[PDB]
Length: 129
Image (cartoon, rainbow, N blue to C red; front, side, top):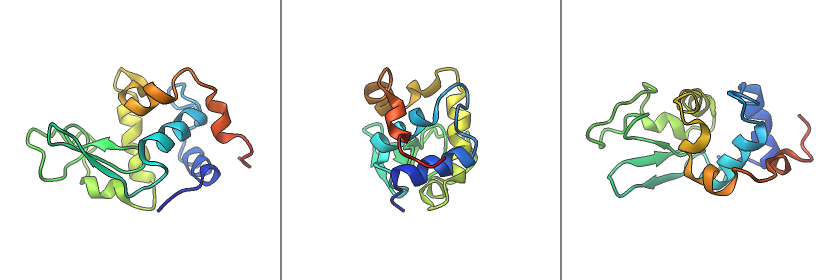
């Protein structure tokens, strides 16, 4: 499913992401935009052989099991395919564990490179929340 900017903001808020660990809804929406372009089905293979899945591009080496990443820790205890669903609950629950991992949202390279330090409020501007 390809989310709309405001529809995603509302779904993330409903799932308790707004200001989770101090990160605004704008940070999370900005991260989804640049990680997957709001597409729940996005996947990207990495050179180390691992693969990133979903709207938040969660990596298979540590967070989910895709059956083809040797040395996977599967810290979110879920098959990576569960992260591509139209319902974002699994992606949200796993992201909460990642963001609490000690490095905050810096774990998402697109957020660090494209959202961090920018007017992230623009991402939820105009939305009925």
